[PDB]
Image 1 (cartoon, chains in turn brown, green):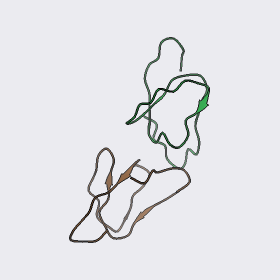
Image 2 (cartoon, chains in turn cyan, blue):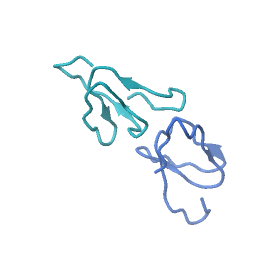
Image 3 (cartoon, chains in turn red, orange):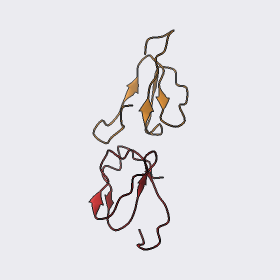
Image 4 (cartoon, rainbow over the protein chains, first blue to last red):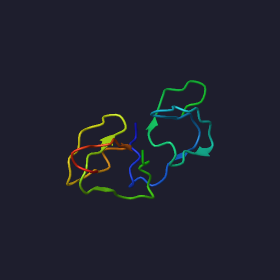
Length: 50
Length: 50
């Protein structure tokens, strides 16, 4: 759970699946996480290594 | 629930009580919220107007 602090600025999703702390919305790369997803949790994917 | 995005930079607690999204830790002014408290929710206090 990488805290989204003001210091990190921006984070990109190169090739993998990431989830939010609350919604845990499914995301498919390539795409920018965007500041909307406040918290960035994670899970161990199988098909594509994140 | 003011999302703590990189655009806002920093936010201060002048005189009031604020809570985090998950922990909802009790905070009494004056003090800085700090990036640790990631998502800032709120509640209607009575004794001291936030």
